[PDB]
Image 1 (spheres, rainbow, N blue to C red):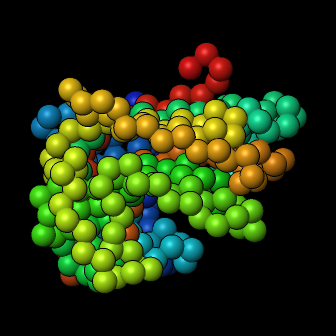
Image 2: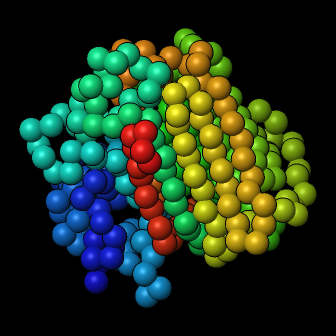
Amino acid sequence: PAPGDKFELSGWSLSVPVDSDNDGKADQIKEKTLAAGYRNSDFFTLSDAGGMVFKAPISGAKTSKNTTYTRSELREMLRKGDTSIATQGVSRNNWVLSSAPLSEQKKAGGVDGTLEATLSVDHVTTTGVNWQVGRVIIGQIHANNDEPIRLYYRKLPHHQKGSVYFAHEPRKGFGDEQWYEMIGTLQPSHGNQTAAPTEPEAGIALGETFSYRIDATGNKLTVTLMREGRPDVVKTVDMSKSGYSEAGQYLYFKAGVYNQNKTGKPDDYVQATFYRLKATHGAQR
């Protein structure tokens, strides 16, 4: 019984942090294989409660030399296994913003986008250097080379509750990375490791169900955090100067766990369970 039996996964590929051909690259599971019921008892499973469970230890294979952190994470693939469609570029596999040139929109697999997830963060690292410990990225928008958004959950080892924040990173040369704290704080950061934040009283506990929404409409980025019985937390970001509407830029969502710790105990880990995951595109969404 695997996630593909319960979730429609034809529109994603998966990477898990094990390297089967010993080439230094983490395994990549293609859409068709994923959709047909791939599972890995260590990294990617279907829970008894019908959740898609991603797990990534600190030590493990990386997807490429371009990252220093492990992940068990989905990559949006609008081509759904059709190998005649390019994985990269403004093709039917990816999407672009509605602020992009009409000519790019016509070549893309979608225009604008929304990623919705309902999940729990089950475990985060409790070992490592003080600016890495407890961090996990649970959703992203990725582009050709840069990251329009990375959404973080972070819980410190001595806290009961965790924080939620995200980065908006303009393309290189288009401006400095922007950080947005939505619940609690991202402290302690690499920038001041002497920080000693108190427990985020509005924080999210391990195992507590919550939802997010990541929307890109034209140059407007909207991130929404939802908890049953509580008001939404919402942050809006203007991306008009970030370069992601330029010709040639393509976008795709990612979701799962991306372990932002490379210094703790090797079998320490992050894990999250996704009960719902939906990516949509187009004006009618």
